[PDB]
Amino acid sequence: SHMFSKFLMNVKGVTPRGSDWANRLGPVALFGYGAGMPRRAPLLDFFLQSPRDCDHYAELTIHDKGPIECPPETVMFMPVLNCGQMLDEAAGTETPTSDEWYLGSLEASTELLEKGYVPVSVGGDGSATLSMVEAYKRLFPSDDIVIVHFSARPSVSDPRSPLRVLLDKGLLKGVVSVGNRQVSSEDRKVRKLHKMFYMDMRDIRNDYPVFISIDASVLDPAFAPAVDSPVAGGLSTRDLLHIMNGIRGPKVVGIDVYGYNPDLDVYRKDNVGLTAIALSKIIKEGILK
Amino acid sequence: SHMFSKFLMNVKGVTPRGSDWANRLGPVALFGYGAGMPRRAPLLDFFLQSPRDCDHYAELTIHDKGPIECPPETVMFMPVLNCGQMLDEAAGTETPTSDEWYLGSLEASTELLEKGYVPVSVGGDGSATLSMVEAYKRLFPSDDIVIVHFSARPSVSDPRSPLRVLLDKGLLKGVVSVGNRQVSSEDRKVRKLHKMFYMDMRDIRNDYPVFISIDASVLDPAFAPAVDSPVAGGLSTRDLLHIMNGIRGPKVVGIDVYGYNPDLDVYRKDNVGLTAIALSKIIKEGILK
Amino acid sequence: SHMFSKFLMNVKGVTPRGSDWANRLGPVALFGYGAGMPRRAPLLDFFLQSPRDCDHYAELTIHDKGPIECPPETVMFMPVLNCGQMLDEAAGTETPTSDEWYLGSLEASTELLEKGYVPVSVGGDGSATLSMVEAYKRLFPSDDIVIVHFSARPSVSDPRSPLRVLLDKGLLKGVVSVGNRQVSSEDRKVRKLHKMFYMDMRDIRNDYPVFISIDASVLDPAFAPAVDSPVAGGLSTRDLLHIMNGIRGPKVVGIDVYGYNPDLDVYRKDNVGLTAIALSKIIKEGILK
């Protein structure tokens, strides 16, 4: 798409992660992804205006240009690179197709992963799980990639769905699905047939690189109302942050936080979305690692 | 009332539960009850448009005509009969009185119970607890009926209130009141005087037929804002679903889910009520048995 | 301020607590405090229209004139004196300054504490923590005052902030900060330097007089959306009520419930604020002691 051109022109030329990072986790690179959601994507911009003070005793630090410097030892920063929104809000109305959102997301993730940033794609419908993990396996076909998937639904009955696509491509050496509460016979047959683990409503303890995929639908509609067909009986924001805290790994391959649609949110009297508040926290503590 | 005529004409002629059910639980028969709430009652209709996929590994199946067939053994369906709304939305504006809502609810429940459907009355103010359990004791005066009551208040200080009426009629061999957090000296005197059990904010393990009465007021106002004088410090939707899961019995005599008023709800930006979402789940997993 | 004149004229002449109270806890004296929030302060008035039935088996009793009588032994009442709003809604538009809000709050608290009422200041931004505990130490400089502080932030990095001011004045023999989830390096340095205890997201067991300071920001934005920069991952209303229940002491020096701003709230379809509902409960069970 001509829409991503300016995003694309930007992702390429970011000064690579240097030798300041030796056997070091990070850095993180952030962008806004808008597939399957309305044309206006705040949330990213809402996350950038949010407190930098984390739940745990580390602090986010946001940079637009490179190179960026590594913190030392015991004093914790968390330097995050803002690549901004995929969609240029000033270069047309020609909104991309699923192939265009994908090819770009694949190209961004690839160009973020090449440089040693941990990619984090925020917004959209969850399609940016497929592309980002596929950029990783392209780069590192030797690395075993697993996925920790948080949603109200397994999101696997449909062959188009991004986890179903990965499983069948044998890119996934395993799927951990957490929070599921809308399970059909389609989801349960595909479950024991691809031997994945699940926890419907301690330590993960693995040496396998973790992709983290977070559907806002996993929370309760009370905390995250801004989803398609919201599913009650869900997680509190704190419930997710707890379980998220306990994810183990040698490294995170990437993070896709999706499912949020401004039009479906419950709003304060000053026009702030409950789901924006909730998810803005979720992204923060997803970066903290 | 002339309003129920079409509902009444309909409840009578439903093809009875057959020999497909031998020593079998169910089937379920659904209707919408509107006493003490505005004339428009969605929720029923909102429940019918909701996902059929339960929290637990069974699936609801909704039929308008009879007879319906019984599932086999290990593969779980949950066939539910839609009797629709009491109030015909096209036969007048003459909204019934408390005697009319009662006489009908009594007549529906009686005509649902005669045929071996487990009645489930959705909407209203909780008056459809009194009528439905009284249709049961009319049919089965030998059967001991207990009630598991979920509300923010005991709803017993007032002699008009539907549990207070049953207790004094000695139809109730016991009351389990769960979730209470607005208790007056009126409620507490009537408590130790009618020796009922309560749990204000494991297994029930009884052989006594269970009526299940669910006031949306039992949840938190965060999850179920759509109630008269909402009471904070309440249940999450998941909290109720847990405690509900643990109800024991030889059979359920019926289920009344009430307390919901569209006018009092908090709404998403697309006009969906938080309480509708919450309660639509509650009814589902109330049928699952 | 000329605004408080009518409030001031009123606080002075309240008939003192008599000999009906001998080695007795209470009574309580209530007023509405509006510092740092819009000119309209409902909440107080919303609390007065709320159910008197507590979570625990005691009942609030609200009196406007004095003297009031003490309950006997095992039968529990909780007689609370309504001093109304600081700001007279009919004597000008000249809204006070931070010195005026303070001098008055200091004068009210002093004139409430002199007479043996436990002061409870409802509304505002939390400034009514500083004044009320300083009226206490003026009266009783011998008494060791500690504070149990509930907020999303430690509220101590800023030298203007009311707990930071007390600590440095050595009025505080200790600070218990509960619920914190936005902690900067400013908050953490000031923490181990003033040796206070904290619990970010059994019995307190102390003989030290307790001030209770409650920022609505401590709850989750799902339960209490009506705060400045709301912080997700918070307490449920029930979570706070539990932890609040477990506060120990020889006496409470006072209670400031703040952080609520009508303009920032999520509202039902009938214009009731979720935060009003939540906080109206919080004040109730804060008085119960």
Image: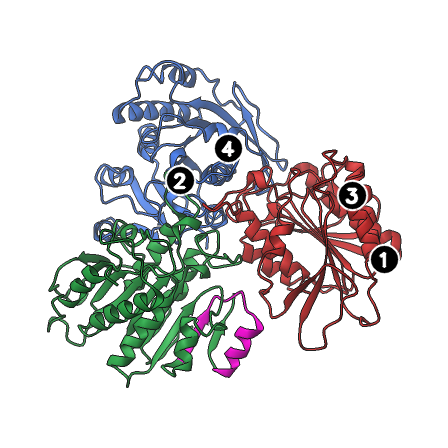
Chain colours: A green, B red, C blue
How far from the left and from the top, in percent, is residue C172?
30, 40
The subunit carrying tag 1 is: B
**Stretch in magenta:** A174-194
Question: Please, what secondary structure does the residue beneath circle 3 have?
Answer: loop
Q: Which residue is mark 4?
A: C23
User: Which comes before the other along the chain, label 3 or label 1?
Assistant: 3
Helix, strand or loop for disc 1: loop
User: On screen, B116 above or below A43?
Assistant: below
Q: Nearer the viewer, mark 4 or mark 2?
A: 2
Subunit ID for the residue under disc 4 = C
Q: Residue at x 78, y 70 (%)?
A: B24
> Residue C274 versus residue A76: which sits nearer the camera?
C274
The residue pinned by badge 3 equals B4
Identify the disc placed on residue B114. 1
Is B31 situated left or right of A185 in this image? right
Q: Judge depth for marks 3 and 1 and give the one in front.
A: 3
Q: Tell me if label 4 and label 2 are in contact, CB under 8 Å.
A: no
Residue type at mark 3? Phe
Residue C242 position, x and y percent, is: 49, 49
Relative vertical location of residue C120 with respect to residue C87 in this rendering, above or below? below
Image quarter hosting the N terminus of chain A: bottom left
Circle 1: residue type:
Glu
Q: CA distance from mark 3 to mark 1?
A: 19 Å
Q: Tell me the residue at 75%/33% (across/down).
A: B94
Residue under numbered circle 2: C226
Q: Are marks 1 and 4 in contact (CB under 8 Å)?
A: no
How far across and down, in percent of the image, does residue B113 sit? 82, 57
